[PDB]
Image (tube, rainbow, N blue to C red; front, side):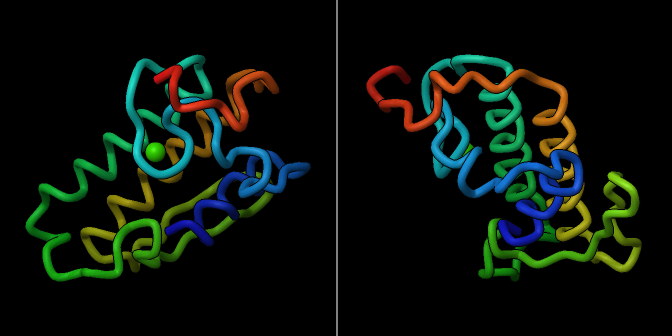
Length: 123
Ligand SMILES: [Ca+2]
């Protein structure tokens, strides 16, 4: 979950401190999400939100109250690449992949310092 996701982002964007730079970005980067994403970074977050939401409709994820933000999985970072571990059971493997996709997206889009701390009246 989170602790793991923060590391995935640091794996790809080494200079970052994720919970500081990507927290409260746009309408999607943070808890919840509503409106239209303000940019590509925000669209990344929207997508991940939809993935988590999707992890929910899976029989494999039904029995894990811990929640994906805190549903712990195994992965690795070796020379800036993320690898989800085969040892992850069905649900965690799916959440892992959602987080890998997002950390990769984040590293491929521009950061607009105009959208952090964005007021939720724009969503
Ligand atoms: Ca979100």
